[PDB]
Structure formats: C-alpha cells, structure tokens
Length: 89
Image (cartoon, rainbow, N blue to C red; front, side):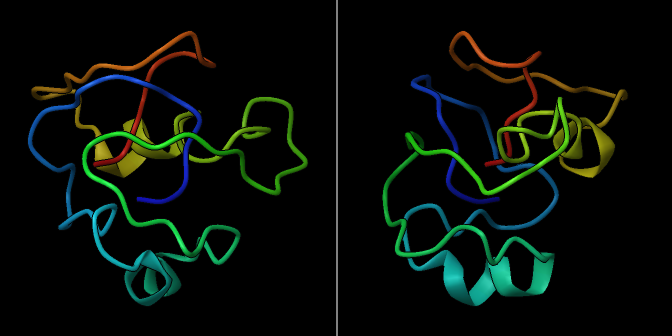
C-alpha cells in the first residue's frame, strides 16, 4: 500500500496489513514504494506517486494492486475516478 489519489471506502486489506493509518515508510519500504511516506490516514488517502510509466503514472491503483493486492479470485474495492480501479488497502 501507499499514498494514492482517491476518495472511497475500501474493503478488507489486500494481501498485507495496509499501513495507511500508521507510518507506511516502515512497511512501504519493504514493498518497494519509497515514493510514498508521511502518510497516516484511515481507509482513504489522496496523493500522487513519482512514476514515469503511462498507466503506473499514479501509484499502485494502476495494475500493481490487481497484480498482487487484488486477486481475480475475489477482487473487489471502492475508489474514485482513477486509472482503472485497483487500490491497495
């Protein structure tokens, strides 16, 4: 998980315990999203990520989530007008 630009209530965490609430700098560091830090909020955060790709332009909402966070087995979550719709937490 990490800083994302969206405003919606998501369901249970993805694969790992989303540190959205607390300091992600600790957890995110393990995931590989150092581009996000100082973000401490409940199930809802608004912010962009330092990316270059076209789709990944944002943060993880792109595909990263559906790649691991979200599973085709029972993928489901809420978000705002963003890339496609694949948040983390």
